[PDB]
Image (cartoon, helix red, strand yellow):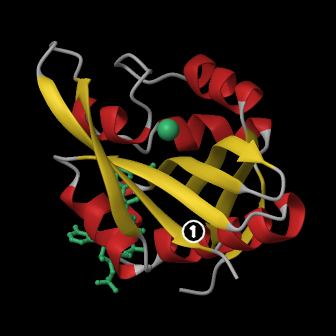
Amino acid sequence: MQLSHRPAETGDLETVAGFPQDRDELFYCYPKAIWPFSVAQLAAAIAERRGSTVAVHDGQVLGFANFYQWQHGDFCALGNMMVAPAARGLGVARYLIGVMENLAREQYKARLMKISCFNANAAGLLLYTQLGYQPRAIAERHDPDGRRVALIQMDKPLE
Ligand SMILES: CC(=O)SCCNC(=O)CCNC(=O)[C@H](O)C(C)(C)COP(=O)(O)OP(=O)(O)OC[C@H]1O[C@@H](n2cnc3c(N)ncnc32)[C@H](O)[C@@H]1OP(=O)(O)O
Ligand SMILES: [Cl-]
């Protein structure tokens, strides 16, 4: 998987808004969104966030991520991490997380990256563990059916 990256563009949003395959996946990567996902919901997140970036391979947009918190000299918090279903398990998220780590360091002078994953998202928890993130805290949250879930907050030093 040779991959490139660039800022997200308007024409990318239809494709990216197709990445979550079901209500669970949408909850995991964007818990304030409501199913079905739409370009309007994606565009609204982009407008409130920073660093919205796509990963591209062989002319296809395969991954998306951004920051929902940014604090210069301090940390960024990575969210909306989503990969095309036909392209999972090929390193897209690993590549994109590295690009976002570099952007945090270079543009934000961040010392730390924060992420939070819902307990049911095994793939996400294992992704960030593989990339050297460690768990710090667990917070109670609710899913769209009002059921109690656990949000696992993790972080990683950027040096
Ligand atoms: C902070 C957040 O935004 S959390 C939200 C994460 N997003 C979602 O859950 C939305 C739906 N899911 C997806 O988009 C994807 O499955 C992602 C983002 C979780 C993973 O993206 P991928 O590009 O498939 O992951 P990538 O291939 O880069 O794998 C990197 C690591 O993730 C983990 N991983 C990825 N998929 C799986 C899986 N199906 N089962 C177990 N571990 C997995 C492994 O640790 C893997 O490392 P390895 O292959 O060296 O063992
Ligand atoms: Cl998010």
Farthest residue to the right: give it: 107
Q: Residue at x 61, y 17 (%)?
A: 40
Residue 111, relative to residue 152: is it above or below?
A: below
Q: Disc 1 marks which amino acid? A: Ile
Residue placed furthest toward the left: 147
Q: From the top left corner, tell me how far across and down residue 127 is, in percent.
A: 35, 70
For residue 154, above or below residue 4: above
Residue 71 placed where, x, y %?
77, 46
Residue appearing at x 70%, y 32% in the figure: 46
Q: Quadrant of the C terminus?
A: bottom right
Closer to us: 15 or 67 = 67
Q: Is residue 62 visible?
A: no
Q: Position of residue 17 (x, y in %)?
A: 51, 35
Residue situated in front as seen by the camera: 78 or 6 = 78
| Image: 133 above or below 80 | below
- Mark 1 and ligand 1: say if the CB distance to the nearest ligand atom is below 8 Å: yes
10 Å crowding of disc 1: few (<14), some (14-19), many (20+)? many
Label 1, on which residue? 97
Rendered image quadrant of residue 31: top left
Along the horizontal axis of the image, is 93 left or right of 69?
left
Q: Quadrant of ligand 1?
A: bottom left
